[PDB]
Amino acid sequence: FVPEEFWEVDASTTTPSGEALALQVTHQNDKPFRPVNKEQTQAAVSLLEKARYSVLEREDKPTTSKPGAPFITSTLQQAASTRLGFGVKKTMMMAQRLYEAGYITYMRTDSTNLSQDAVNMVRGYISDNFGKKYLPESPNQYASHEAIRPSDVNVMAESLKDMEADAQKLYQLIWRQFVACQMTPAKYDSTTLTVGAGDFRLKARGRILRFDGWTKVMDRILPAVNKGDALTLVELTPAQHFTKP
Amino acid sequence: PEEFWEVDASTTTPSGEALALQVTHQNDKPFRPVNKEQTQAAVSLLEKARYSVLEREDKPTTSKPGAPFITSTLQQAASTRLGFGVKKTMMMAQRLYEAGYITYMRTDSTNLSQDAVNMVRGYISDNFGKKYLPESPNQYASHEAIRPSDVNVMAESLKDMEADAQKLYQLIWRQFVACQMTPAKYDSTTLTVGAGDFRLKARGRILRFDGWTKVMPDRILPAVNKGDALTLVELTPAQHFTK
Image 1 (cartoon, rainbow over the protein chains, first blue to last red):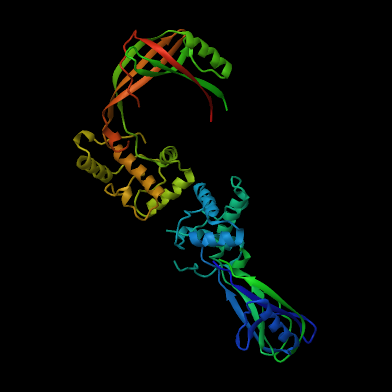
Image 2: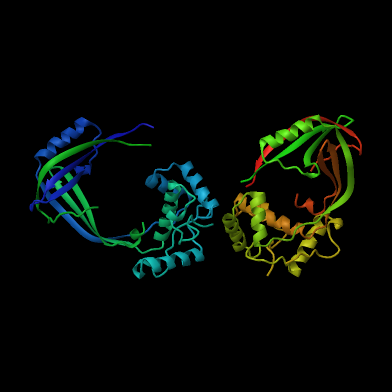
């Protein structure tokens, strides 16, 4: 594998009211902005430094995010790696121990299916511990033996006195994914700002949580600015990156 | 944990054949040292003794099969023979039941239905032979026992089950078929040896008819008679702890 070099440019600006607004340069000449070396970035930066910044478009809309499916072997490995920093073989050793102790279901599966007993169990837990608004009218179904889930939803990670810290973290991950998969969607009020500067286009995205839904068990607020408003550039910050395997 | 020792004695018969012995008594009382000093004291004595066969008992023996599984005995057998914990065993048994491969897994009864008895006796007659089939169905001290739903379904055929689930089904299947088969027969032997203040023993048996062990799978003591002199080769002490 050969790492590919690419640069990104962020711009700190101030709204007419004086509030801070962070932007990411996305386009240059209507084409995706992605310089590959320092000189190219510097050339772009020199242009952005003199350009006039103005809000081209502001889009506000409600959005929802649904929970993910309960774990299968491949998704558990991916999540344990991303969230906990566990390698695949370590994740599988720990999952096998949790299964052999009877804490979770069989760990080698490619099915997201959940038995009626498991659905009854988790929906009861949700009704008792979270509330009616967190419970969908009908069980949530997922594209797809059974998924990897706790054997007893009433058993919490901290109660596994026979497991070391990382094993408890893995159980907690499995437990949270399973409970969340049967909860209602999270609701947000999203905002997207599009800014123009010379032959450059920049953007900022933000959202405000209206209902937590599944996120209760398991980006920022953009300042007020309308279309046509002028933004004052404060600082440009280029960043060098390299792709990974 | 309680520390206790044992002592094994390797000897040779007049013909020169090896004979392994275990020390069982000392001064007519059960031998069971609790430390290294006690054991070493016994070893020094055994090292200077004359060894001779005090008695040889040869007799036929019988081994009957066990009852079909109930929840508690399945858990015990899965632990002892397969190394499965209780929770794991019950999770797998539940899946086998839900798939329809075995009968309900929560039971305290060793009873078998007339249909199940007819089915397994037919299997035995077809696959093992008349000497493996008792005149009347075998009865056991005691809903129904945990058994396969279809005796013609072999563990190897459960494509939808992982290896350990197949091992569990195999265990249940073998226990069920064996429980309706005839006793195994052996010719047993017990050698009692005298060595100074100690008594040592060796046990052996030869299979004469496999019976139930045919579906659900010791030593052969060398030829020696009462009065035969034995030559001590080596004494081997062993330290143990209760678990």
